Amino acid sequence: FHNLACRIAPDYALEATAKIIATAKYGKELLYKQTAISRAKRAPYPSRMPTGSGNSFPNLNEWHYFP
Amino acid sequence: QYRGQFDVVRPVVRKLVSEMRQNPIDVLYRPKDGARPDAADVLMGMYRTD
């Protein structure tokens, strides 16, 4: 609703006050914060990549790259 | 996660074994300060045998 304010303010010939644009900027980041953390995610080992002698139970030799 | 095995201990061990494996070392059975010289040969022959 802060971001809403900014968007509709020009309808009424109006510049949104500073504190508002600030709070909108701030708010919009926070919406995505927890999502951004979710979307981090490391990709798996590559098509190649040896399996590793230390790793027991061979399963798919080398690395799965798909699993 | 990956676990490689890049040891360096083996080569040492291999070396040590190879050394002891080329210096056989067995039994002897010398006679004794008192006994007759031909004391050992009987036993030794038996030992060597089995």
Image: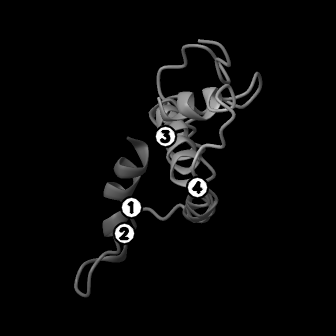
Q: Amino acid at mark 1?
A: Asp
Q: Which residue is labeled 4 in the image?
A: B10
Label 4: how many Cα within 10 Å (few below 14, some 14–19, many 20+): few
Q: Which residue is labeled 3 in the image?
A: A27
Label 2 resides on the chain identified as: B
In this view, A25 is above or below A9: below
> What residue is at 65 percent from the left and 38 percent from the top?
A14
* Mark 4 residue element: helix
Q: Disc 1 and disc 4: Cα gap in Å?
A: 41 Å
Residue B41 is marked as 1
Q: Amino acid at mark 2?
A: Asp
Toward the left, the furthest residue is: B34
**Is label 3 or label 4 in front?**
3
Residue B38 is marked as 2
Determine the image quadrant of residue B8.
bottom right
Q: Earlier in the sequence, mark 2 or mark 4?
A: 4
Label 1: how many Cα within 10 Å (few below 14, some 14–19, many 20+): some
Q: Amino acid at mark 4?
A: Arg
Disc 2 + disc 1, Cβ < 8 Å: yes
Determine the image quadrant of residue A42.
top right
> What residue is at 57 percent from the left and 65 percent from the top?
B16
* Mark 1 residue element: helix
